[PDB]
Length: 52
Length: 52
Image (cartoon, rainbow over all chains, first blue to last red; front, top):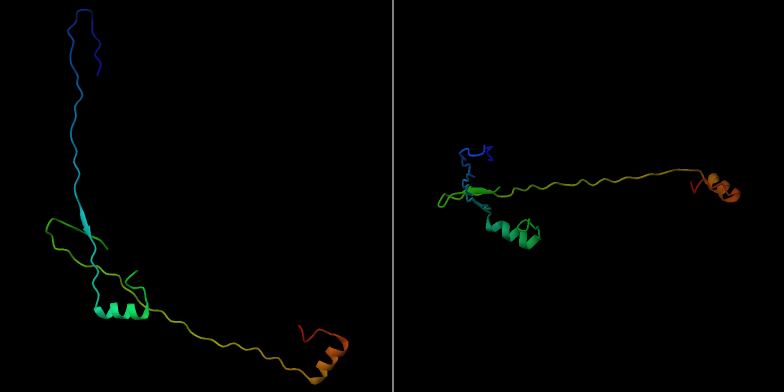
């Protein structure tokens, strides 16, 4: 901030203050489980279940 | 769905789910009955009745 001062009046200081802020780190996973029966059914009959 | 995991938190599973749906089959008929005298009237006068 600025300060208003007289002719030989004593001057002050006012200085910028700073602080840090920090990230977190999040790991996200998805796991889908199915029978090998479902792989056989899809690859024979062309369902597109594994692709969807 | 995704799951948020720590550095050695235990990972879980979430899998897609599916179901089938089925059509019906439906047979539709229209039958219109007329006298032989109507066919003769129509084709001799050009009535257009049988075209309609």
